[PDB]
Image (cartoon, rainbow, N blue to C red; front, side):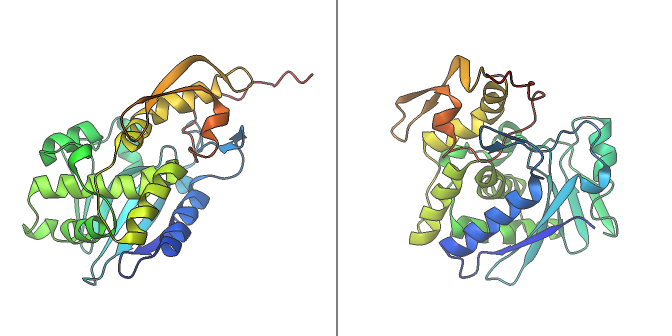
Length: 263
């Protein structure tokens, strides 16, 4: 019932990956909510269960497939299916636990991990931080195989955690940030894997804060600046939504849009 977007790593190109990421953004947002030219994801409050998820079917050159489930309210990967087994991250609350019962309903083996799916938890399991995990098309190809072989014991937990870390950044974070989509495009164009630099990491860590700063701003002006990092690690101060229009593609819903006092 939920919409399915397909991507393969086999022969992937900047164009095929761009088409994918545009398609995932098109299914995450409805057009209802755009502030400063920046689309907002649906509000969790009152969102009917039939509109709550999207499915991303990944395939690779090894001829394997897995299907990730993303929550439209936050673009979070909440679990995945590989053939006859599905695996969900530990839910944050009761209502999320009910909602994930609506995914992969005819799968014969359903498991809920005892750990949640946030980067900090997944980095601990992986034994490596984001900044030491290479991304690109090779890493994605390998991550699709790792997720596929988990149920049979082929995949060690640390390699499963690392594989989620790769998927999340190359799908969810790229949908959230044109900047991160363009970092992936670069790696795919040259077929050269590399770990994310501080510009990528600081944007990932700041997504919620930036979403709230933009939605609470006075006509786009932040009451408090947010500090990001450039590629070389130097500080970049954000004072206004303006500088983020080329950078952030989607925000999480944080407040109602005020009745704009119009001059």
